[PDB]
Amino acid sequence: SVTGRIVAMASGAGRPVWGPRDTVSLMRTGFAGNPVGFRSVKLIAEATAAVPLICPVLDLLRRPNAGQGRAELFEALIGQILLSGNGYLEAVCPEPGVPRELHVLRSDRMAVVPGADGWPVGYDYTVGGRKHRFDMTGHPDPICHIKSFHPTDDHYGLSPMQAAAVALDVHNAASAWSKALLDNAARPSGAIIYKGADGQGVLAPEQYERLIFEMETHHQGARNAGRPMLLEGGLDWKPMGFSPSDMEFHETKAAAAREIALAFGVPPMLIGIPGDATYANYAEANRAFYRLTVLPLLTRVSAALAWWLSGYLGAQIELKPDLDQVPALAVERDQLWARIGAAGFLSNSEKRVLLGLPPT
Amino acid sequence: SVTGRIVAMASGAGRPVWGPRDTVSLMRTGFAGNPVGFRSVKLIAEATAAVPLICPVLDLLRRPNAGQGRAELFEALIGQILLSGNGYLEAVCPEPGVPRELHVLRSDRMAVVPGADGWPVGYDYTVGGRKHRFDMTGHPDPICHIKSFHPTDDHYGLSPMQAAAVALDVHNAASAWSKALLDNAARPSGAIIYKGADGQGVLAPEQYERLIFEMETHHQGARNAGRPMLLEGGLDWKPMGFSPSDMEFHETKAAAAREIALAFGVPPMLIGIPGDATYANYAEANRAFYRLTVLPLLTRVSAALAWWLSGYLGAQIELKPDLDQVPALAVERDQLWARIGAAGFLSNSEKRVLLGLPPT
Amino acid sequence: MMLNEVTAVPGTALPVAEFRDHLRLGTGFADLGAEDAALLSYLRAAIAAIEGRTAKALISRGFRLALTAWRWGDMQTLPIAPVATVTALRLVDAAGVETPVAAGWRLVPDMARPRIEALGAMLPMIPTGGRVEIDFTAGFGASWSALPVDLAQAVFLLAAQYYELRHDGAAAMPFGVMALIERWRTVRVLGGRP
Amino acid sequence: MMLNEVTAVPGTALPVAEFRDHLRLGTGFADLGAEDAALLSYLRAAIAAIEGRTAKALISRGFRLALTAWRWGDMQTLPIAPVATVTALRLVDAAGVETPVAAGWRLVPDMARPRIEALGAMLPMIPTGGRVEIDFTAGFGASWSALPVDLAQAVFLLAAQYYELRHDGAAAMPFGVMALIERWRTVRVLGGRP
Amino acid sequence: GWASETAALSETATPQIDRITIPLHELAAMPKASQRLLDDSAFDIETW
């Protein structure tokens, strides 16, 4: 905070700081463009919305606004964090405490203002040429700004799609390689070469319609596969091939489809990409998914809702994921109940306090 | 100590020492550039934040400042240690004991000052051309400087990304090899060679629009795949191939994608890179991750918070990782509870004292 | 990109009196001028053959390079290679108005890459539907003596050939016509986008 | 990089009186009749064919090497190979202030790779837009007698060929024109970025 | 431009983008200090 004043002047106080320009184009080319970048965010954002929470405040979260439910809110919230590294939540307060409206402001059209002491004073929702200038020079601070970790930038997040932005363009263009190869390719199944007495000679349109009708009827198609095809003088049939037949950038697409899944943190088994068996039997890969890239993400966002929404209340509230009755963690729950349940030496109430039960 | 006093006057007392030149460029090319270097830091920094701690002081750590939570602090702290080998924590102390502000200062813009006796007297936060000159000539010493181990340098860390700086540039350029190969490549699916009566001869634009329209309509596309393609005198169709089709630096990228994961110490199974099965079934590789590169890293930073923050208190406090109810170490907890629980010879209270229980 | 010539060569600058010494016509005859109408017809036919194989100019006549869209964002390599003192990048409009522009463009002289690189990181913009003609005088020198002599010899090896055989009749030298030309051709290896 | 010659040969430096002896002395028709100034025009055409294939200079004419950006950090190989004594390394700016430098560089002479090779790692930087310009005198000696005589014979084997037959007519010698040149060509194997 | 209704408005001038180069020159000092003078004196010469 003491050094906060020094970085603020360099950027320029009172003026909007934009950060990354090409953020909106990674969405259309990397999330609406390829299925791997599409499925990876949809797999996470529909997983963090499904996790229950532990606190009143959750009555706001259950019904944030019209037409945007509890689970639909976090899909919009985490879906901006995975896409552009930043999450925004406007609170509309007709009432003084616990404001009854939440709105995920998209992070394409939002810009920060550094202000005096380096910590932000303005946020600017910029649609068309129109700005809004939300104000942070107050106590309730009407927008929570959830940052992904960015080491070099002081105001935004890193957005894992930016780290995979080369592997998206490999997977977008290798998939479009095979598309435009199926659309721009002339393979013939042969060529009836007609030289003539000279090195060059055309055949007359009388002879040419004769050549079609014996080729149309008697030689093409499945039903004429293999006629013995008499070739008189001058004529010759050179059959062409198609030498790379399968596998046009097949492994570099399948390797880039795994590096996209690597950056968002989904395992290759969940998304459905082919590859070597790393995880075994989905009791691991679903448990690894909710432990390395979902529950760390959800306990970081819920820790920002636990502090931003407590600024509207008087008492501070904690708000964490449940990490109980989330059915992907049952292999960590069998393993912990059967450990203490088999420990017969310590008594009955001495293990209800370990497994989390109210003792009797 | 005595050696340090001599070391200072060699480099120059009272003057800033910068150290690494490229550490601002390895972040953009190695942490915002490739997914493997991105995920490797995110896999560790989100693991050290999840580990609970054992001690008042932790009330500061739970809520250091506005907009920067407990888990968000260590992601910023370890995210500077893995990136640039140095961690910094500014403390703002309006009050004499337990200062209520912590700030992860980024290590790009921080520089040390050796001072008189070799141990540092100044740290210089330099953004733009503007400095701050924090002072270490006092007892509370307002910045904890967490060093990674560096054998050759006396003031900084080694930053595992610097050790993997060759394998980053292999993985960045092999991935950009396939991108620009899919973007700069002219493969044709053939070539209609037209020599003529001479060795050279063009065909007239009347004949050329006839040649396009019989190629556009009747030969290209999926629906025209394999027409018999009459070639009169002079014309000839040479089908081209594409001899390296897949696998452009496919293994040298995948070997470099493993050496990046090797340097930070993550196993290949957790991050999702392909490779031979070293670990078996994720009960090991997650347990290996929280034992070779997370908990040794976390017990080294927590040992520095236990000593820097105790300089603000009167009594010294220990602060260590929990090494209990961290669910990756459950296979080391099954193995130790079933060993002593099955040891029926020693009595009931004689094994509650071994497993860490409150005795009865 | 049209690249026409404003003015041709004067004809009096061509060495017809020295080409006649080359071809061994005759020394002291009283006629001496029955070939003057045709000798410069083959010198202009051999220079224009070597101006196209080498992309050089050789007499430094004035050119007019009328083009519409810039080939690259700032560079704009000129076709005719040995240049000096680009006169005017007058920027015509969609129709009519021709405004000459100093525009902050430079000229990078070279025999291989005669660029017109701009200094403000962007050449003067082009009114949509309008061309940008560039007047420049490109060549080695004004008179025949200012040429590289091996290229001047390649005209004399070639225009002597057109004088000695009229139609395409077939007929190995160490430094022939072709081997003198080849250090003046343009050596390019780009078929790419930029 | 224009690299125009400052001054050409005087013409009186060329061995026209000796080339008449290589043409027909000791055996021949007589001294015979040869247009004297014609024989000077074939020596200048044979030297300029061997100045291009060897990248040598042979008469020690004055050059002017005006190029925009330094290729290496410090090296700057000079193309015309046998050099001696940089006249000046004056440095003009984008407006033409022409501020010469007199120290910071030491020409390292060599028939293989003549250089500029400034002291340390600092070679005079270029004013933005203001091309650097190097005047030097490159070649063997001032007179014809200071040349390597095998290279001088390659001129006489070639200038006589342009005298003996005019057009490009067909006609494997052990040390021909080509075999006397190849120990003076520049042998380079770099097609790379440095 | 203020666009009329019957105008069929033409495209306007895209603002020219300037690119001004910082050359980033060097500045160095090379003082020559004696080894005996650095080894004998009471002052910290490498610091001064």
Image (cartoon, coloured by chain):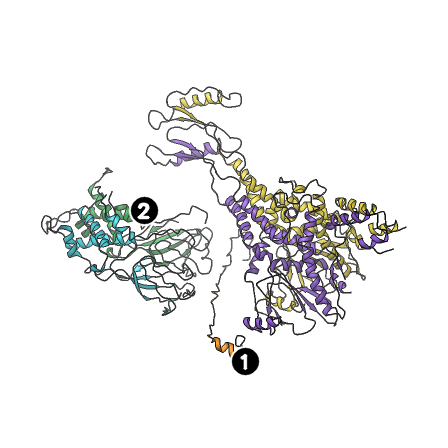
Chain colours: A yellow, B purple, C green, D cyan, E orange
* Nearer-the-camera pick, B117 or B175: B117
Q: Secondary structure at mark 1?
A: loop
Vertical placement of residue B30 versus A205, above or below: below
Label 1 environment density (alpha carbons within 10 Å; few <14, some 14–19, many ≥20): few
Q: Are marks 2 and 1 on the same chain?
A: no
* Nearer-the-camera pick, C13 or A11: A11
Residue indicated by mark 2: C53
Q: Give the percent coordinates (x, y) of residue D26.
A: 11, 51
Question: Mark 1: which amino acid?
Answer: Ala
Q: Is residue E10 left or right of residue B70?
A: left
Between tags 2 and 1, which lies in front?
1
Q: Is residue D108 left or right of residue B118?
A: left
Residue indicated by mark 1: E42
The quadrant holding residue A139 is: bottom right
Q: Give the percent coordinates (x, y) of residue C26.
A: 13, 48
Label 2 environment density (alpha carbons within 10 Å; few <14, some 14–19, many ≥20): some
Callout count = 2
Question: Mark 2: which amino acid?
Answer: Arg
